Every structure is written in C-alpha cells, then in structure tokens.
Image: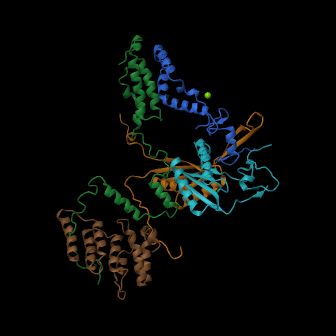
Amino acid sequence: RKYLFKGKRLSIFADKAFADEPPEPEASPSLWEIEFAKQLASVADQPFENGFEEMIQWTKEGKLWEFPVNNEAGLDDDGSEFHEHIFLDKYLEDFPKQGPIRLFMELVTCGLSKNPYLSVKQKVEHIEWFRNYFNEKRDILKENNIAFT
Amino acid sequence: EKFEEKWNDILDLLKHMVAQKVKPNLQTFNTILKGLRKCYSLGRIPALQILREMKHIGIEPSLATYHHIIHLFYPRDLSAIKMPSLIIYDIMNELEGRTFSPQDLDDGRFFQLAMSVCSSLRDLELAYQVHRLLNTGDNRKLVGHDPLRKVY
Amino acid sequence: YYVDWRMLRDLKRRKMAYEYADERLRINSLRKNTILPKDLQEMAGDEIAALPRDSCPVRIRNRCVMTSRPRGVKRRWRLSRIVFRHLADHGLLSGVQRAIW
Amino acid sequence: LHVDVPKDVTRPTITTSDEPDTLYKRLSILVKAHDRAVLDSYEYFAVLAAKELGISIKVHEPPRKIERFTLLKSVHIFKKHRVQYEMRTLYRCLELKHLTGSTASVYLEYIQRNLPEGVAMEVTKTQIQQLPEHIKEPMW
Amino acid sequence: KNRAARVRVAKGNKPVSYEEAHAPHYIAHRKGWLSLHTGNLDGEDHAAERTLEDVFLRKFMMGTFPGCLADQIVLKRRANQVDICALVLRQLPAHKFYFLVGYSETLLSHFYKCPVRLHLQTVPSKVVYKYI
Ligand SMILES: [Mg+2]
C-alpha cells in the first residue's frame, strides 16, 4: 500500500544524466560553507568510548606520534638530494680556478659536504661569506701575488 | 493563508532551480520536508513524492530525511491511535544493515524519534530492529546528544 | 627570576655565543691552516679579537640548573651532586639506584 | 555484553597498491629496560604476537650493562666519605626473519605502541634488493 | 650517621607510608621508581630534560591539589604521552576534581607540547604502612 519507492513522484526535476557538473569548490570556502561543515561534525560528535578512540583522535590532530616510529617524520630538508649536499664545487666558480684560495676553499667545501647538521642553503651561505671576504681583501691578496675575481 | 498557493509557490522556486541549471542537494529536500511537518494531514502524499524524486535524482536519503517523514506520519499528538500507519516497518527494512554518516543537521534526531514510535505501537520486535540498526558500523554516533540520548 | 646573578650572566654568554658561532667559525677557519698568506691570517687574528668577549665560547660554565652551583655538576642531568642526591635517594630519578657490590 | 552486541563492526580500509613490497631478510629489535621482569612480559607478548601473525622469531639476552659513578656524600668537606650510584640496563633481542614491508610495519606498530614505560626499542631493519640496473651491465 | 631520605624514629606515634618507611638503599629492592622514562637507559638522550620536567610536574600537582595528595605522584612516559597517577584524599567535592583535572591536563599539554592525562585514585585516608 504505502510503498516508499513505488508510486507517483513530483516529476518537477529530471533524471540527472549530468551529475555534479559544477565543482564542489566553485569558490574558496565561504564562511557559510565553512560553518555548516563544523555543524555537521557536531551532529556525529560523541565522547570517547575507550583509550583507542582517544588515541585515534590525538593522531588525527598530530598530538600523538605516528607508528611505526620514524625519527625523521616531517623532517625534509627542502627536498634536497645527496648530490646537492656532497658536490659543492659548482659554487666555487667565482673563486680563482687555481692557487692558494682554490686550495683553501677545497678544504672548506670538503667539510661542508661531510656536514649533516647544515642544509644546502646554510652550506651555500658559508661559501658566499668567503667570496665577499676575499673581495674586500683584494689589495692584501694582490701584494701576495694572488688575484681574486 | 492558502496551503495550495503556498505549496505551488515553493514548487515555483524549484522550477527556477532547473531554469537556471542549478541542481538540488540533500539539504534542499530536507528543508521542504521539515516545513511539511506543520500540515500533518495534507503533507503525507506530497512528502512521499519528494522521497521518490530524491532517489531518481540520485540524492541518497539520510537519517534526517526519514526523521521528517516519521514526524509527518506518526504525530505525537495523534488522537487516531486505532489504526496507525505501517510506514515505520517499511523504512526499517529499507535501512536494515546500512551504515550512515553525518550529512545533515537532523541526523541525530532520527533514532530518538524511531524509538518513541515503537513504544507508542507497543512493538518490541521493531525496537530490536531500530537498536540493531544503531549497532551496525558506527551508527552509535547518531543516537543523539545529552537531551535525546537519555530519551532513546 | 633565575637562581642568582651568576646564572643570568652565564645565560647571556650562552645566547651571544650562539649568535656569533658562524662568524667565529668562518673567521677562525682562515687562521687554522697553512694555505693562506700570513698577512691575511694576521688580519683575521684581529677581527676575531674585535668580536665581543661574551661571544667567546670558553667563558661558558656549566652550573646546576636548579641551584646555580659552579662545580660538582653532572653533565647528563645538569644538576649538582647535592641536588642529584636528593632526587636519587627519593626514587624520583628513573632507573638510578644505590650501587651495592 | 550479554545481549547487546555490535552487528557489523567497521574495519579499516586496506588497499593493495601496485608498487612492489620491501623484503626484509632480518629485523633485529633490541629492547632495553632497567627491569628484567618487564622484558620477560614484553618478550612473551612479542613472541606470542609474532607467532600469531606467522612471523619467525628468535630471542636471546645480550649481556647487561651497569654504569656506576661516585659522588661526595657531604655538602661540605669530608672528602673520603662518598656515595655511589648505578644504573642497570637489561636487553632482550627479538630477531625476526623473512618479513615483507607490510608485515614489518604492522608488527612494529603493534609492539611499539605497547612498549611499557621505561623501555626503549632499537629496530635494525635489513632490506634486500636487486642490483642497480647500471651496475648490472658494465658500460664504458 | 646518614640523614638522607630517612624518616627517623619517633616514639611509636608517627604514621609513615610504605614509600616513606624505606630508606634509599631499598630502592630497586623493596620499593620501585616513582618516575619511569627511557632517558636514563644506556645510550639514551635527554635525561636532563626529563628530570627537570618531573620536578616541575611534582610541584605543579601539589599546588593544584593542595592538601589533597595522599602520597607522591607516579609519572609514566610512553612515546610522547605523559601520565600522572596520584593517590588523592576524598576531601574535595567530586565536581571540583573534574575541574582540576580538565585544567591541569590542558595547561600541562600546552606547556610541554605533549599529551598529558591525569589518573586519580581516591582513598578514604592516607594508608599507613607502620607506626614508627
Ligand atoms: Mg670552563
């Protein structure tokens, strides 16, 4: 008799041959859409039932460590590569191609390649400091027969 | 003043939703049914028609959508208790074993309302189906808040 | 408030040595070698001297974090022998017991 | 619960990828603690857990370490009178074998989350992989 | 004579608890450790930081529950979680404990940036091991 899905319908609308044609984020989430979502969450918001459900919520919030333990979780050094940390001679092009300054900077870049506590950006900054230092000391170097830049 | 005019007006808004190529969502139908709870006597045939259109469009009825149909077919202040409607039995068969998620602001209301209808009809078998639905998956999260959890 | 004025002075020495760590590293590197002209090395010997005295990291002293005691400190806990004994003798340090053998 | 029981409990979604899985030839788990009895209970819990998932496990007890240091007993003077303290570290090594990368993550998570207080783990995975494609063929 | 952590004999009228009765040389023999972390195990770091955090957590709980602590608190660190287990006398009303638990947990989680939980076991009165 009172069949839920058998009988006449309004028929104002038609079958959705095309579905969800406009994207859900038509614009950046507005205050109206941001607030309705918060209310939907409260609809199913019930208190913790055991220590598992509490730890699940802490994990979703980042409060509790993820397992298995990864000692480098969230620790990506600018998405670098091993070759960037190890091969640093590209940055010594401005320096003299030979001579005492080249011999010294070779030692500097050798240590920087073996430094696990510095990022590529910090390693480059050590190189740049010496470039500007010797430039300021152009006159003292020239007396010693060393030509810089 | 006139329901027939009022209903024809609300339908006109729906007709302009298709002229402008705007497709309705769950909230659109949920809003219409919540309004129909005022006219219990005359909203029964309109209310069922909406749910059939919901499936044809492809919108999936949520717990809130049934919460409104129950109110409209099982009034709390119902003098005519001699021959109550049987729709509650059909809905429970439809929702048997399904899992539901928060998709509206009246999802919590459904379970408290379903238990009330079971007590009114003095059918304990139906109460087990309603409670059994609450236990499937994580439906327990939609029982209700502090006021409605103790009533259920 | 820190424990005493001696702990405060040390705290500042530790915060100014961190600021001047890179600088004192780069300049001091120019002196700890035999590859650069001695004229440059003598000049870096003066730039390092010109930096503020509190930048020098050998003026830091390890003091008890709770009593600011200069000597008698244990570096693993940063506490003096006297303060460490109070916590150990009470079962408040995890795994520390008396040594009987 | 006597009469009220869940009907269809929700279970997490595990989707098989198309990437090949890691192959761990060995996986050494060195747990450390001040208390031997805690290691015995964890050794029982871990060995029982490994056996229930199909993992092959062996256990041995590395020699314990005791670190002793001396302190001065008096607050002032009285040099000759000292007090000595010690810390004891006890070890239990769970040597697992022939584990895929999915089996080693779920097992390590399960046993790492249940690591008692005062117990530290030192996992040492040993992966086995083919040779680099360049190395496979000498190229001049 | 050794005066360290010894509740000296009175005339038989001083009620000492199990923890108080035992001198330091019974640590690891008859009585255990009040704090359990992995920072004093061999080849482990951050002993200084765990020990300082404990000292504060003990002074904080005393002031937050003044006169309501029957015995010393027990601190348990697992992963980044901190757990405070305290025997508390039944002096205060029940709802006051719910306030102090919510307050002390939230405040200590935002101060050490770790999840902190408070576990309270209520006793009718202090438990006396022996009268000394
Ligand atoms: Mg010194």
**Which quarter shows the N terminus of chain A?**
bottom left
How is colour applied across the structure in the image?
Answer: by chain
- Apparent colour of chain B: brown
Give the vertical position of B53 relative to E9 (above or below). Answer: below
Q: Left or right: where does residue A101 sit relative to residue D67?
A: left
**Residue found at the far left of this picture:** B19
Give the vertical position of B124 relative to C56 (above or below). Answer: below
Seen at 33% across and 80% down, the residue is B73
Residue E80 in view: no
Give the vertical position of D44 relative to C11 (above or below). Answer: below
Give the vertical position of E95 relative to C23 (above or below). Answer: below
Residue E104 in view: yes
- Apparent colour of chain E: cyan
The quarter of the picture where residue B143 lies is bottom left
- Apparent colour of chain C: blue
Seen at 77% across and 58% down, the residue is E130
- Apparent colour of chain A: green
Could you say which is closer to the camera, residue E68 or residue D91?
Answer: E68
Could you say which is closer to the camera, residue E126 or residue A106?
Answer: E126
Q: Left or right: where does residue B95 sit relative to residue C29?
A: left
**Residue found at the far front of this picture:** B1
- Apparent colour of chain D: orange
**Quadrant in which ligand 1 is drawn:** top right
Position of residue A110 measured from the top left corner of the image (x, y, whole percent):
45, 28
**Residue found at the far right of this picture:** E11
Position of residue E4 measured from the top left corner of the image (x, y, whole percent):
74, 45
**Which quarter shows the C terminus of chain A?**
top left
